[PDB]
Every structure is written in structure tokens, then in C-alpha cells.
Image 1: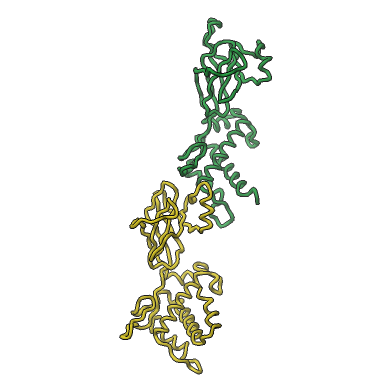
Image 2: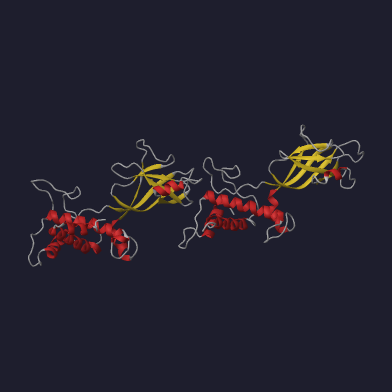
Length: 238
Length: 226
């Protein structure tokens, strides 16, 4: 469903049927609420605990098809452009894509074959570097986030005498905003995430109704305006 | 089996990264447990203490085919000069320093006194120290033209007590096996002083028994406190 249909059905669900009808929302307000609902729905559905079903990214066909249109595969760029201070002497720094929302799978192709990257925690880092070996298992590599500016920088730790040829990253693309109308104005150009032009929902139509319902709920919570509504409907921001 | 096959079979037998509870090892841990299993197995085989086999060093064809690749022969004519022995006619010879157990040990003699028998090969008899005093004068078990007494002493030495001069000393021992190292280990690490990859030098017949014992040692290591 296109942006016109979002706005029309938003009006229908918000104030065209309600008894003591409230003031209609401006298109900037509707676009804001739709974008917020979009991010909220994505974050609810990625985490099993964030939604009532207890199901995460890949725990049912619906959850697969939800993010099917948001999955992207790219490559990390070796960060030898400038010098830097790595926490680990034997770690190669790589830069992830700018439009990165969540990492779900990583892999590195070395001279010794492909190796799955395991994102090790800081407590797991401390535990693993206390052992005599201090290297990953056969078919894996280790990863820790390093000094990041304007985009995520990543430290890859592979076994000794191994060189990395490429670093593929299956991530979830950052959702584009939903903007109903050209927000250009003579009084000042307003933007949702830096874009004022019309922007369609770049996700599957399976969750367009879901985003609309969340937008309506947020609109009515803002209308109520008490601390209670904001606190209870902020629990789902996550 | 090769090092790659060793690691892959180790993972398969341990059910690494399966759905059921399991154990995952680093290649260093795999190397450590494979080496421990190797050396335990060959020592138990040599001593005949393995209940599965229950046979000694060369007691059957199976054990021959297992430990055939550790049997090393050695020759030496040099004698260590400054040492204190238990008899005047005591000569000392160095050991190759990689020996595990001496299995054949013979000594050639060069002396004028045993005329026309010169260059006689002589059986080195390992003799305990209890028997030494009462074996020095023994004409049936003591030193003679066809028999030499060897006593082990410090610094990897062999004190050969003979009535005649000893010219050459021949050995056939079991050697240190090369460790089973599946990866070039980082700096500092080593197994038996070896840092690079090291393939098992025994026959493939015993490689799978070594793998089974290494797997059992791994489960014991992870499941000795639970």
C-alpha cells in the first residue's frame, strides 16, 4: 500500500469514525508517527521477548517474510586508510556499511577457507585470552567492535598465518522513512531522517497494516498526553 | 589419516556444533589430547598393560605393525672419560637422548686376550645393582667374552661392565614419537618442543584407536568435576 493509502487509512482509523472527533493530524505528524512505528515494529519483531508471540527474526514463516525485504548483504572495507590503535595486536580492522541496522550473519574468506565470525563478548574475550591458545576454533573467526566514528569499525581475529580476502556481512538494512508528501516548504524544509521527498515503505506489505496500527496507537497516546500513556507505550520502543 | 582428517574425525566423533549437548575443542586442545592418547597407548602397548590388546612390544603381528615406526637402531664407538663407576673395567656410553625403552642392546669387543675370537658380538645383559656384587665373579652370569653387564646411570649414560675391552656399542630402541600437531601453533606454544604441524609417524591401523582414546580423554577432561 502506497503513501496515499497510509495517510487515508490513518485518517479513517484515527478521527473519521470517532464520535467526538479530534483534530486531524498534519502530514508531518503522520509521517513522523509512521516512521516511529516502523522502527518500533522492526525492533519488536527482531527480539522474541519484544512481541507477544515470543518469536524472533527466524522463528516462524511470518517472521522470515517480515524482514525478507529488509535483509541486505555487503562487504566490509579494510581500514588501512589511516593508522589506528587496535586493542589486539593481531586484529585486522574492517569498516561495516553505513546503512547497517543489525548484524545477523558474518563470514570471512581466508586462504584457509571460509570461516564463520562469532561475535565474542567482552567477558568471553577475557576468558578466551586467558587460555594458552588464544585463537578461534577450526571453522570460525572472532570479532569485537573497535573505535568507531560515523560507522561501525570491526576487529577480526583469525588463526595465525592466515590472511583475509573478503569479509561479507549479512545485515538488516536501516529502514527508510515513510513520508506522505513532499515536506518542502517556504517556511523551512523539515525532514524525518534527512530526506524531505516522498518516501514509500520499503518493507513487505505484510506489515504495512501493522505499522499503521502502531502509528494510530502512538497518535492516540500522544493525544491523551498523560505520563501514564507515554510510559506504558514507551515500553514497546525497546 | 592426515591432520585434516584427524581434526574432522575428532569433531565428528565429539558431535561438535550439533543440536545435542556436545564439546568443541581448539586445534591446540585436539593436538594435546591426540598426543596424550598416542603416548599413553604406545606405552600401555609396550608394557602389555592394555586390556584390549593384552600383548607386549612384539608379541604378535598386530603390535609389530603398530609400533614398527618407533624402532630405531643406533651405533657408537665413543666413550665418556670422566665418570665414577662400580668397577675398574667400566666404560660409559652416551644414550641418543630420544630413547624411550631399549629393546635390543649388543656390544662388539676388541681385545687381544680373546685370541682368534676378536670382534665378537657380546650380549649386553641389563643387570640390577643387587646382583652386581654377586655377578662380577659369576662365571655364568657375569662379564665374559659372550656377555656384558649394563647399568643405567645419570645424565643418560650406560655403564658397560666387561672383562674385555668394549670397542662398539649397538642399540635398537623405541624412539620418542613425533607429536600429533594439527596446526602451526602460535609463538610460545609447543608440544614436545615442536611448534609446527607434525603428522603421526605410526601406521594408519592405530590412528583410529588413538582418535578414540583422545576423544575419551577429552570427555574426561570436560567431565571430571560435574
